Image: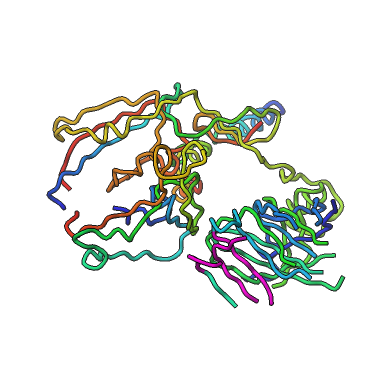
Amino acid sequence: DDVRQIAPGQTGVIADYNYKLPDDFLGCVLAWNTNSKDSSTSGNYNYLYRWVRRSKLNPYERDLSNDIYSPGGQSCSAVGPNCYNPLRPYGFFTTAG
Amino acid sequence: QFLSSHRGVYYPIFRSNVLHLVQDHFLPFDSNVTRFNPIIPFRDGIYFAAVIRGWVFGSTMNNKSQSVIIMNNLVIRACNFELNAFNCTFEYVLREFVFRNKDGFLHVYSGYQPIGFNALKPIFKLPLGINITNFRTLLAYFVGYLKPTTFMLKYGTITDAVDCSQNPLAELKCSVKSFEIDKGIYQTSNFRVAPSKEVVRFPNITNLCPFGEVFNATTFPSVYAWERKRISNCVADYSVLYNSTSFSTFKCYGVSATKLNDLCFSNVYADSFVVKG
Amino acid sequence: KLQDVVNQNAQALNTLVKQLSSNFGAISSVLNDILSRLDKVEAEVQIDR
Amino acid sequence: VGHQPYRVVVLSFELLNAPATVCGPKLSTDLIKNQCVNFNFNGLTGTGV
């Protein structure tokens, strides 16, 4: 469902928090299913995505960081109330839609 | 402190004898340039001038955010430095330089003169893709900040560029697209002042729209009996919904989705139902 | 004749200024709402129109 | 996947010269006058004094 977001002008978790494309994109995008390789019956959790960020990424930018996030700008210490981990696993299953 | 005379011109493609007018992040003529080893804010690019070994660009410079080190023992490495290198990517093997960061590319222009005017030829366009808000030097040197302005360069070597926002004569020169002007009186376009600040005014609304409750209802109408709801007096925040509701389709007609976070509507109607794939 | 030329100039200027109200087949005749509603890449077509 | 339920919600907006009801998650800024300054009044983005 997130493949649609890989294109100039789209908005969403992937587009604005993980991977952003320039508005003047000159190139191509290729995508193919790998449910037999990147998935497992018990769940392949090695793939993660960032679902929180104070500001959207600039085009062609990377955000390697795992600092604990707090909506209110507090001094978080561990996952819990008002202390979220910005990275969440995909959890790919073989039988999922 | 000082004044930069007519320094800080860089190539913003090949062209020759064109007298080309371009709007970009340039250093205004006769601008203030500070003189100095502290942490120097980067803002929208810098013009550095000068024993100096290299530079370190980054955001936090504390190993919690990727930073790039350029140095000469030429080595360029982008990693999570302590101020040792882990989870990282790019690796490679009078003084003036210009540093810009556009589309994740760090443009580095260089120049050297035996000490005026000189155009800084491009050196690197490094694919770093990192957020730069601070930098430091590695060892008297001058630092200036680039601002958005429109210049008229001559040109494939640039020669005698002119800034259109500093004098009435320069404004006339830029509006006529010629460096030689004969005696006379000419009308000119407004190159003097451009807006810098922003004034956002939105209504006094604090409630959040109940998208989570609506999209999580246990029952939805048949397509033939689709309902309608009027959404009002709430802030449309789709970001809170990224935690769920993958939204296999988000086609927006008329407005653009990216603008939905900076638009206000007079009336919003939500019609819900269930259909086939 | 003199009043006629004065009126001609005034009417020409008035027509020129009133021509801005026409949207020329685009989303709207105003740049502000086009730029505040449509993103850059899509807004290019309206701006060109 | 074709023969699977797909919950659909259609949002219809009215951008009229009437009091705003639904707004984005932007923060209002102080008023600056007598300066050529970009402004954003309830979605009206422009440049003026």
D7, above or below B147, in the image? above
D49, above or below B136, in the image? above
- Give the mark count: 0
In the rendered image, is residue C25 in sight? Answer: no
Image quarter (top left, top right, bottom left or bottom right) of the C terminus of chain A: bottom left
Asked whether, in this view, residue B4 is left or right of residue B128, the answer is right
Q: Is residue B75 magenta?
A: yes
Q: Is residue D28 magenta?
A: no
Image coords of residue B78 (percent x, y): 56, 66
Q: Quadrant of residue A84?
A: top left
Q: Quadrant of residue D21?
A: top left
Image coords of residue B271 (percent x, y): 25, 32
User: B174 or B144: nearer the eye?
Assistant: B144
Asked whether, in this view, residue A8 is left or right of residue B84, the answer is left
A66, above or below B109, in the image? above
Name the colour scheme.
Answer: rainbow
Q: Which residues are magenta?
A: B66-89
Image coords of residue A76 (percent x, y): 48, 42
Image coords of residue B209 (percent x, y): 36, 29
What residue is drawn where x is 42% and y is 54%?
A18
User: C14 or B129: nearer the eye?
Assistant: B129
B131, above or below B207, in the image? below
In the rendered image, is residue B144 in sight? Answer: yes
What residue is drawn where x is 30% and y is 54%?
A90
What residue is drawn where x is 40% and y is 40%?
B255
